[PDB]
Length: 489
Image 1: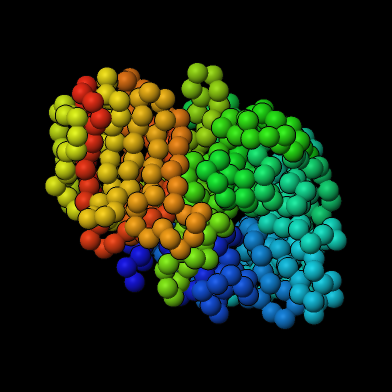
Image 2: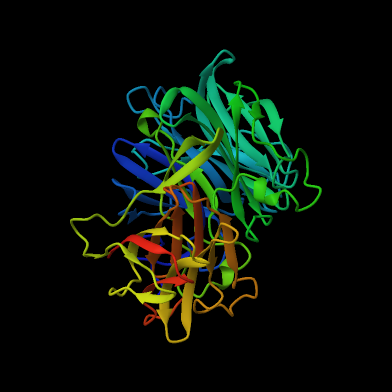
């Protein structure tokens, strides 16, 4: 089990995909997820479930919502219905409610539809019951899915809002309800920005800009498959305002279906790597704190990823916020860190000039957090060599000629299991004060790069050998400096 992540969630056995139902209640974070309880391929979709107190150390639970002969249990969300608006619990014992897509089989009364359904728990997520009146919302569509529900209060009213997709239409549909059961259509958003795949797994939430509670925007999350900047599945976002009925985007670059690929780098990407999909947020987290987690794989090749009895991991969870630099509001995302100082050993390389060539770091690193600050200066390139062994390495390179940071995994290890796997992922990263700050998480099958304190992220799976633990800094040309490198494992 050489690829088992040490600090990313996996099921002990079997397949997972999209995170679902993310909710905090009474001190416990609940992670649900698309899961095949019966094998390592996609199928028999059911909501798996894990719990934690800290978003980092998870206890895998029984399945929460099982498939049956009539329905597979596709993606969705959960809310704490504290005042029992749904009537599914009582005032003294209010329900935790999952809103999920039923994908009906040929045996069901409404075969072939995807429609929205409820399940609920009266014991803080230990046991679950499907609502007898499912489905609660049906558009007679095979592709109406992935409801994300939140409470809204404003001039229009005070009610639950659902954001869901008509996936094939590449649109988000918004609905309201007083009780989670009877829903009324509000509006339809899109298509806009990235549209070269089906839209999936949306979310919609309000965030302050640069910590000013008077200056908020709404963020609409839309996942897409394929059609991502790096090839295959990805997440995008829009920044704007929600009036209680419709979302008004202030960051639309192209309206309608794309006409070509020419504006792709201008769309709002959640990540610039291959393996960050279906990211959505936690409900019921106090004081507006916004936490997301993604499925750390890509539909291009997830089935072939060579992990044996289990398939796929989740990303690190991220705290998401808004920031303005040079007048444009954009998302900032930083991992919730799994490697504290007290528990981990630490190696520092202090400030020094970098010669043209490779500087080895005296630390084997495969389960580690690397913080590095580089001043590229006049050099042509600077970066890190990650997960290096005799015939393997993953190269993270900042190119001063074009200002792009790239992760090249073409020689990273096992890559032949799918022709779409080897790749080089690029993102523009302006220097600040002439410097580049990177926080890089290495786990047994993954690299997560957070650049410039979360302005740009890049998440790629890798499958290196167990002996491929070498770490190095490199420069191409003279003139670069190392400000500091810290590695913790």
